[PDB]
Image 1 (tube, one colour):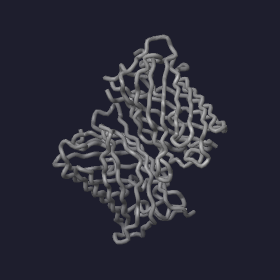
Image 2: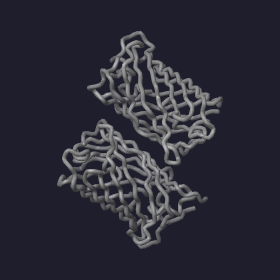
Image 3: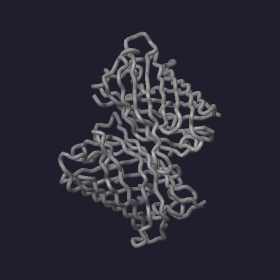
Image 4: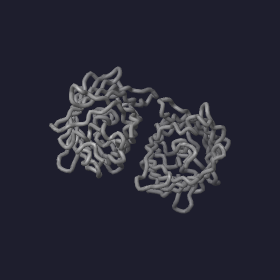
Length: 224
Length: 230
């Protein structure tokens, strides 16, 4: 059984599948970094609770876009909204604000996730994010803009193990040869190795992304 | 294109597809009214703007669950968020609070929909809802409870008409007690085809929408594509 609520892992579990409108395609750092990819690092501060630190490698492995993550979580309260499993099984729309990191040749992002709590309150998860390209080639450093997200979480009736089904749509707003790798439907593999409060777990996800419409379709299975 | 934003029509465009947990099946008015169906009437008041009045007939026509709606919108302002198309193309999660309407032999509901606006603010839409059975059979009058919703809106890249692709999950909650509680429940054991037809007029601008898809009430899932028909 997952030691934390599935919604708290959503943002950690491939922004290269965001739909950048034609007038913004010169601002799409994520696709410009492919195929070598990028390292995505976050600190996620759950207000009045613990923190996640994550480091992920996002790159192509042949035809598959892979997101391989290490997650370390600490300082969660036993009676809080996370370890107490008080979060609703849903996900709000967020705006992910992106700025260029002209020192690392990459980007930073900042946003605050709002997790609905079963008692009507909101649990904030403040995200600080930095992405650095792995490859040598030129990448696109964007003007300030944001990604606008939508996500629904469900369960596979035929699935038996602890799992999460996710459908997500993301479009860029607010204003490369790598992008040519995203013209069709691309298979996705996500692998997460986690430790929260000393509770170790793993998550494996598979699905597909369609960047032409900003769509992600994934099923995640836990192991503990 | 439609004269109003697609998100403002989401709630008007089949709560019989909500997942009612087994311990709450006695509270599912919507399925109990089937197959004869129910009339669903709403007043939707947009804060600092106009209002929609809707009357829908929701019933089975053969194998298909049909939602046929008349919508009249009045008193909208030209520079507002609706006629000015300033709403984000998304839809927030809501709780729909349902209570028995014993004096109408049905149910009523109150909730506020929060439409995100492009400038970062919110457009509130106060919903009042009344559902009355069409048929003569016995219906289930529920205890107070709510429906919890999740919805995503998207587009079909090969569709030139104004349209909205929708996926929704809804589950009932708020009762803690714990077969089929109505004969109409039996009609929703499978995946049911859905037809939605909306005839609208907002501030004198006439339009229409047709949607088709499927609903799976055992998991609470709705999958539909809506297209402008005028």
